Structure formats: C-alpha cells, structure tokens
Length: 59
Image (cartoon, rainbow, N blue to C red; front, side, top):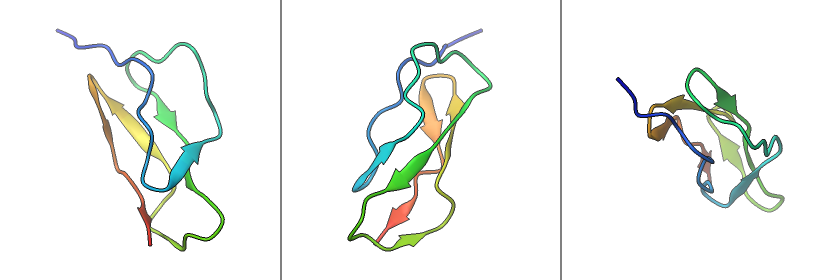
C-alpha cells in the first residue's frame, strides 16, 4: 500500500510548531509563517503518503 510519511519538509517562509518524531499516515502538522510575512490561507498541512498536503501562502 504505502508509502508512509517521514519528517515533514520546511514550508514557505515558515516553520513548524509541532515537531514530532513519528509521522506515519493520517496526521496533520502546523505550517505557520514567520513574523514579517503576511499569512493567507490556513496554517496547516496533512500527510499524503510520501508528500504533504496544503502548503500556506506566506505573502
């Protein structure tokens, strides 16, 4: 079936607040932007096997 997810990548001029060690399948993360970047969209991502879903717009 797979693929299982591993550590989520970095995001557009942002970081993660919930940096865990075990990411498999059916998980979400907190794709937050930094200070000096205006955020548009949600601020989270989801695990889609090997890739992640919804990246934010930190404009």
